[PDB]
Amino acid sequence: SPEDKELLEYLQQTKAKITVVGCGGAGNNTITRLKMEGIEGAKTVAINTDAQQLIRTKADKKILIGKKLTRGLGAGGNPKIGEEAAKESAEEIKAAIQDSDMVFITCGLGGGTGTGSAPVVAEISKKIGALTVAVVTLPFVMEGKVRMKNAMEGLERLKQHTDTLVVIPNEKLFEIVPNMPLKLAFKVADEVLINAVKGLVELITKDGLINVDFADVKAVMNNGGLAMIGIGESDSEKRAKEAVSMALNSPLLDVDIDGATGALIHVMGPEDLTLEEAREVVATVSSRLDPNATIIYGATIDENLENTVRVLLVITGVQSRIEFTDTGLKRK
Ligand SMILES: Nc1nc2c(ncn2[C@@H]2O[C@H](COP(=O)(O)OP(=O)(O)OP(=O)(O)O)[C@@H](O)[C@H]2O)c(=O)[nH]1
């Protein structure tokens, strides 16, 4: 009906449709925490090639791709199987995000499924006009040369189908956290992924002390190119003043940012989070990027955050200072 159709539309246009998609054991592992812990204003879809894994995964919608190829046992770190498996189910996937204004594709680069599928999804995402964003991590050195090699090649493909590509050099984590088994190191990674994907999405969908227009988010990330996360947090007197400079100095931000084209700041904190602090954070990051960089900044209150202010930094437009290498990212 015409009268209804018009009401319907008003509804849908009231807010944006965000969809977070995680591929592979890594991606699925992230999708579950977001789902359980809850992710404001975002739909969660988890696609894997391993049925057993997809089973113990929590999400709004699950999808088993590449039925033929993989007997539901995984692509065995073979990217090609992932890419093929995806396209097979390129349809049931397109329906999973069919009406999204923005779609996030997250996973852990280096394996088969993730490295493979991640880009296929990115392409499907874009064909439907959705603002496309990926948030993937690079493999640990302990993982070997072959793993990294594939990761990088996947990271390449991904770049050709994304509006703003965010990568985390899992390796740099040891420059923060101490030495530890490849098992526990993964946990550290697990955290960071959640903080980045959640922190991003929620910078758009959660109500904070500052208005964050989707029109601006869309503008700044429509050409994000390559972007790098940066995390920090303080407890002291000048927590605001610290968390910022701590995130700005996070080894995860492996690149020079003097010529930052854009940035997405999401300052989080306790009930006593003030606009000055938020202001403080933004002011700092602002004087580091291009004097004319487009900056999107929010400031919410975290349910459980006694007296700690966490800060998420996602510097976009840094592809001009990084060089893809079969062994990883080099600071060109
Ligand atoms: N944070 C996190 N990283 C992990 C974990 N397990 C694997 N990864 C990372 O993600 C990369 C690939 O993800 P996998 O979990 O192997 O998933 P997949 O590649 O989709 O699976 P296959 O194609 O069958 O090999 C690995 O090289 C690791 O970097 C985990 O549980 N947590």
Image: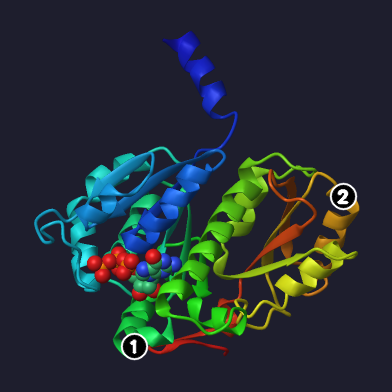
Quadrant that contains the N terminus: top left
- Report which quarter residue 276 is drawn in: bottom right
Q: Which mark is residue 275?
A: 2
Residue occupying image coordinates x 83% and y 72%? 287
* Residue 155, position as x, y percentages in the image: 40, 74
Position of residue 72 relative to residue 130, above or below, is: below
The numbered mark, 2 or 1, whose residue comes first in the sequence reads 1
Given the image, on which type of amino acid does mark 1 rest? Gly
Q: Quadrant of the C terminus?
A: bottom right
Viewer-side residue, 235 vs 316? 235
Does residue 82 show up?
Answer: yes
Q: Is 262 left or right of 189, judged from the image as shown?
A: right
Judging depth in this view, the residue of 147 and 326 nearest the camera is: 147
Task: Specify whether tag 2 is near ligand 1 (CB below 8 Å).
Answer: no
Question: Pointer 1: what residue?
Answer: 144
On the image, the x and y values in percent for residue 135 come to 48, 63
Q: Quadrant holding ligand 1?
A: bottom left
Q: Position of residue 102 (x, y in %)?
A: 50, 47
Q: Quadrant of residue 96?
A: top left
Q: Secondary structure at mark 2?
A: helix
Amino acid type at circle 2 is Leu
Q: Is residue 157 among what the camera can see?
A: no
How busy is the neighbourhood of tag 2: few (under 14 within 10 Å), some, or many (20 plus)?
few
Q: Secondary structure at mark 1?
A: loop
Q: Is mark 1 within 8 Å of ligand 1?
A: no
Q: Nearer the viewer, residue 45 or 123?
A: 45
> Which residue occupies the foreground of this view, 330 or 132?
330
